[PDB]
Amino acid sequence: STGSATTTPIDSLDDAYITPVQIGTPAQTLNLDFDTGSSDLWVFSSETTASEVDGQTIYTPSKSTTAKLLSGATWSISYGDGSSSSGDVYTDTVSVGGLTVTGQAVESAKKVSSSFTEDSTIDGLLGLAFSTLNTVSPTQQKTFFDNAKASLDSPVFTADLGYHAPGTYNFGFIDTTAYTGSITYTAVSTKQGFWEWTSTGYAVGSGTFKSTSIDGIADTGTTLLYLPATVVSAYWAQVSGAKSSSSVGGYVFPCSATLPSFTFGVGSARIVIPGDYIDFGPISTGSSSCFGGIQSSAGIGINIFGDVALKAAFVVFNGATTPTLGFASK
């Protein structure tokens, strides 16, 4: 089997991407944030504290003939930005782009933090990291991908995110029309539960490539590119007027600037992020100070190849016995 679904930016900055997911019988379609940096599939639901719902589409298990309470199971998760959610668990039929899993753990939110409430376009998250990070207690649950894997033509999914445009998540096959040149595959460590890999270096604009190992995760659920302070400083030093602002919470730059590209290494191959991808616009409406899409990972504890990086590539998440990551230009 295979699946194929379109993923769509939630706003004009590509702050996140939503993908329609069918849950239950008859289908209830929710728009979920596919997140390769977490491993819980959770949704706004009929159980979510009413004051914490503001425009989201909710899953109502009582209206699904295939929903069953997973008795005793609870979940609770915190994300890198400080947001959080928690609740209980149902199993139900979940389909993505024509690909169906029966008995998928659907984690129903009783509580969500304010930043989730405030994002009316995101109805939940669908985790695509390794199932070892799944937060369901006392019986840990598997991701949609883990459950689907044995049924897939090939044990892979691919992320093809658009710049200010829709893209595609495919399951079970590699679309050879979706990228240019070859896919370069690189080793993955699953030791922390993430799609963790080592970039071979970087360049700023038309500058010389610096060979240097950068350990990080491929995370579709993170908006920006977070790299070591040395690297980030070298990038923003090429933008007149750019500075790190403690009050804003990162690097800002004059909105009148033309940003240089940023290149990262995948083995001997190179992925180029165009300068425009690194512009996240005015820090506040009408400001001439703009927020940068490359930020320091210092104090995160890990480097994150988020959407800013991933949307410049066709990315293969290879879930074979020995997992790997593939990157191609597109």
Image: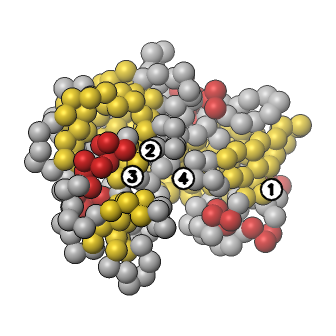
SS label for mark 2: loop
The residue at which mark 2 appears reads as 297
Residue 224, placed above or below residue 129: below
SS label for mark 1: strand
Quadrant in which the C terminus appears: top left
Nearest the camera: 210 or 175? Answer: 210
Label 3, label 1: how far apart the Cα atoms are: 33 Å
Label 2, label 4: how far apart the Cα atoms are: 22 Å
SS label for mark 4: strand
Asked whether the residues under the numbered discs 2 and 3 touch, taking CB atoms below 8 Å apart as contact, a structural biologist would say yes
Label 4, label 1: how far apart the Cα atoms are: 18 Å
The residue at which mark 1 appears reads as 110
The residue at which mark 4 appears reads as 33
The picture quadrant where one finds residue 112 is: bottom right
Residue 57, placed above or below residue 289: above
Q: Which amino acid does label 4 sit on?
A: Asp
Q: What residue type is labelled 3?
A: Gln
The residue at which mark 3 appears reads as 295
Label 2, label 1: how far apart the Cα atoms are: 32 Å
SS label for mark 3: strand
Residue 27, placed above or below residue 52: above
Instruction: Give the foreground label among 2 and 1.
Output: 2
**What is the crowding at mark 3: few (fewer than 14 residues within 10 Å), some, or many (at least 20)?**
many
**What is the crowding at mark 4: few (fewer than 14 residues within 10 Å), some, or many (at least 20)?**
many
Tell me if I can see residue 274 in this picture: no
| Residue drawn at point x = 71 percent, y = 36 percent | 135
Q: What residue type is labelled 1?
A: Lys
Nearest the camera: 102 or 291? Answer: 291
